[PDB]
Length: 373
Ligand SMILES: CCCCNC(=O)[C@H](C)C[C@H](O)[C@H](Cc1ccccc1)NC(=O)[C@@H]1CCC[C@H](C(C)(C)NC(C)=O)C1
Image 1 (cartoon, protein in one colour):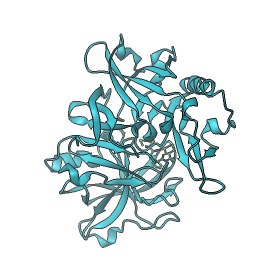
Image 2 (cartoon, protein in one colour; image 1 turned 180 degrees about the vertical axis):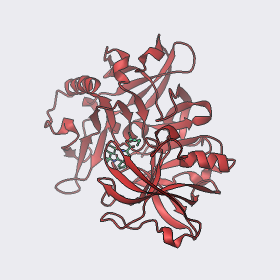
Image 3 (cartoon, rainbow, N blue to C red; image 1 turned 90 degrees about the vertical axis):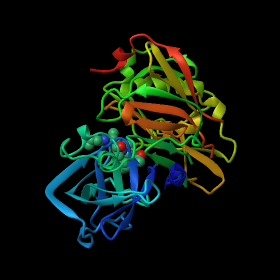
């Protein structure tokens, strides 16, 4: 019954999507951010200025202390805590219960966001990148092994308050339109894929495709923006600045720091070009592309003066650790993390809240060489 999982996600724009879960006995309810960019399941287990509530191990009879510490650093933010196991369930998900590893966060820095509504994080990636090491089985692996839930999940993240769906164990045909296109997972650690071509405003970036995946390209629901390697980021911004030459924006805008407003309903979408990302396909020399609209990479933010002007932020930033296809990229699509077949599927999302596209086939030679080594 995937229908019961539809809309099981929510959150605030730019602060991630979270799902409700329960841990321990009796069940303790908490909101957990869905992160395909990590592999650790962790929850606040101690007081914190931004935590509405937290996991109380003492109150759980099924709690088991592993007597081992843990530290996890992200692109932004970090925490440390005590490892242990307990019973976990997902109210608006599969009707099952499993014992999984849980990191009880005792201390953190720039991790919890003031007013996010979530008190934990669910790393959905592979054990390979779990801390302290790959012997700490990730939550999804425990779920699949302890239950009959198929080895895959799908995410439908809807743009701007924000909502979405995490279908655990399968694909929900009502969450997308058109056909699903699959790209191979290059290696099972992060959900790594290979970008074989990039176009902006219909113009090819004419860069060595390896630059697009330096030093890797991952799909991360836990990162809001689209992050690009330095050299690719510079070329993208240049192309995007030109296409919107009709207008001028502060340098802070192009840094994702500042924000630009406009009269409610007067946002000049026509001046902002679409971005096409071509991904390695499933048959020889075959690829496909997903198109990202400005309505995606221009994240809407709170009005400065008063509710009357639509303000936005450039949701594209620079990266020194490879390409990151974040939420703004995932918003336009229904994304299938097909672990069982080591592939990720993309299809036009059913959530309207204009539209992005997924088209193929296209031809590209030596696709594997686009991957960085
Ligand atoms: C240990 C081996 C795995 C490490 N993996 C990572 O660091 C990945 C690449 C990034 C994480 O998904 C992280 C998860 C996170 C979510 C919310 C808050 C903090 C961390 N998000 C990031 O590091 C992003 C870095 C850019 C800014 C965003 C922001 C703070 C704005 N939060 C969201 C949800 O976008 C977070």
